[PDB]
Structure formats: C-alpha cells, structure tokens
Amino acid sequence: ALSDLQVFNDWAYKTMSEVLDQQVELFNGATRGAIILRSAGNTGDLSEAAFWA
Amino acid sequence: KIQGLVRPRDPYSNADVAAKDLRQLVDNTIKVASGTPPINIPPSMLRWIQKNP
Image 1: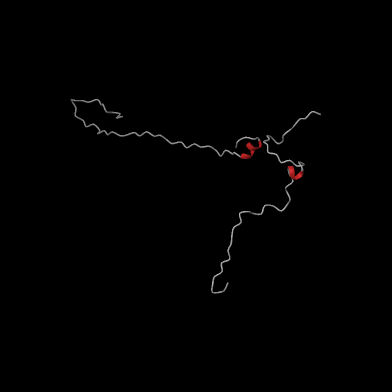
Image 2: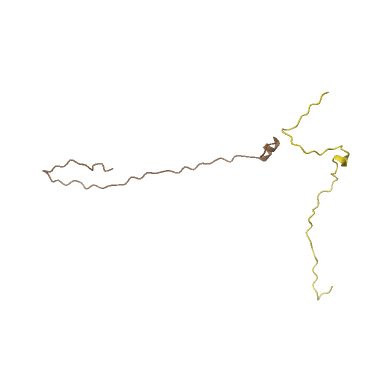
C-alpha cells in the first residue's frame, strides 16, 4: 500500500497444534498385526493366562 | 430455691429478721465440635484394581 493508508497484517490462532516428531503408527494393520493395540480392563499388577501345553 | 423461705417466728417477741432476696440459677448446653481427619482417596489405587474411584 502506502504510508498514507494503514496496513494491518491479518493474524489467526491455529486449532491444530504440533503433535509429535517420531513415527508411532506401528499398531494392528500399520504393523500387519505385529503390535496389537487392544482396550480391556485388567486387575492387579499383571494378568496371567494358562494355555494347555 | 429460697433456702430459708419459712422460718420459726416468735409472736411474743418482735426481733428484726434479715431481709431475704431471690436469685436466679442458670443452666448451660456446651457445643461440641467434631470432625473427620483427612482421608486419602487416590483414584490410582481403585483404578489399579479396576474399582470406581
């Protein structure tokens, strides 16, 4: 523009923030089922499972 | 209660008897303040054993 007029550089607040910088998509299909992300409720320090030998 | 409200009287005599007065006794209901010590309720312990905190 010019000095006579006033320039007002527009601005904005981004809704999306930076999330990560490391590849962490290695679950289920992304890793061909190698690593499985499951949602279940487990009681105690650990959860045992007994399968016949 | 007036301790000597009724007194032996001699009609033949005419001696002065000490003037008496009535006083007022007061009762009392003391207030007692009770409470509970801080009870720790960490959500982590209940969550570890899958219990609603």
